[PDB]
Amino acid sequence: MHDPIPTIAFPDGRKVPALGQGTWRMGENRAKTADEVRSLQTGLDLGMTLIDTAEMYGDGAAERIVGEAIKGRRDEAFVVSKVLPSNASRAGTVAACERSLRNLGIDCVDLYLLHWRGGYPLAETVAAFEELKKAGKIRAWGVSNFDVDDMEELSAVPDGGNVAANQVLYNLARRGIEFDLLPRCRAQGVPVMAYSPLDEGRLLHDADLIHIAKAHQATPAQVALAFLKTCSGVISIPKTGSPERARENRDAMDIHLTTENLAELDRHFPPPRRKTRLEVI
Ligand SMILES: NC(=O)c1ccc[n+]([C@@H]2O[C@H](COP(=O)([O-])OP(=O)(O)OC[C@H]3O[C@@H](n4cnc5c(N)ncnc54)[C@H](OP(=O)(O)O)[C@@H]3O)[C@@H](O)[C@H]2O)c1
């Protein structure tokens, strides 16, 4: 019997498991599709109910993978997608949402993000998000790759205070948001979605993570996710094309990092001591 996935509440009171599933680079290889679908199905069965995708991921292909994986079980998934900033005009956003819904094969996304900051004024994009919400086409909107200054601009936008999430880079190797952005979003009640929680796999070569993994009879990936589980206000979205890895990632929740593991990680992966430029992938 494994331990449960902690839950995080959105501003609107909806709760999701703090461990979800990524999909970037899915749907690029026909030979992997069956496994990618199965990986997401496996994570859903195990309670990794949030799935993060985007219009740009394989230009609709990752969305279609998500659509397969949720076939017969839409109500079990919390589907997140995104609009590219070059599409995030008043009419563009609506048109992009409709494509995503067609690809996903569903009526409504749970959460719809601006993927990063572009040249269209924020009020335009938020206006489109609020109309989609009223139309029953999205349930909530948020943003991604927004630093503090970007977050502040939302207050000048009417309805900008409805922001439901900020999806930014965060893992042991990229702790910059701890200085300012994460504390702001926590004070504000806005979940931070930590993308690339395994630093795209680069963390898995780290000797201190390996050592700590060894002590817990776990894997380095499981340790990287166990750390992020300790962080309140954070939802991590690791991606894997492998159903065996999905199971492994789920079981990262059974690790209880000790006070000494945490000190050692802080020593090996130092927190920012000053404001850091937002890292983006
Ligand atoms: N908003 C944005 O701008 C943005 C940017 C980046 C990412 N994201 C989202 O965040 C998700 C996660 O980040 P990411 O995909 O960039 O990288 P990541 O999840 O940190 O790591 C991905 C890599 O780790 C491997 N992996 C996963 N679990 C493993 C395990 N237990 N053991 C060993 N290797 C493991 C995967 O390989 P296999 O697939 O071969 O197993 C994959 O190559 C993306 O899929 C995407 O949904 C959003």
Image (cartoon, helix red, strand yellow):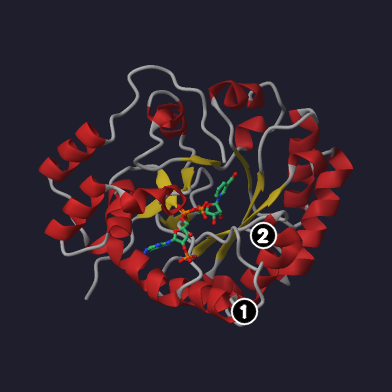
The kind of residue on which mark 1 rests is Ala
| Secondary structure category for the residue under label 1 | loop
Whether residue 152 is visible here, answered yes or no, is yes
Query: Is 218 rendered above or below residue 232?
Result: below
How far, Cα to Cα, is label 2 from label 1? 28 Å
273 or 230, which lies in front?
273
Q: Residue at x 61, y 31 (%)?
A: 161
The residue that label 2 is drawn on is: 109
Left or right side of 124 for 51: left
Question: Would you say 100 lies left or right of 11 here?
Answer: right
Given residues 202 and 133, the one toward you in this image is: 202
Sequence-first tag of 2 and 1: 1
122 vs 253, left or right, is right
Q: Is residue 88 above or below residue 32?
A: above
> How many residues crowd around disc 1 within 10 Å: few (fewer than 14), some, or many (20 or more)?
few
* Image mark for residue 31: 1
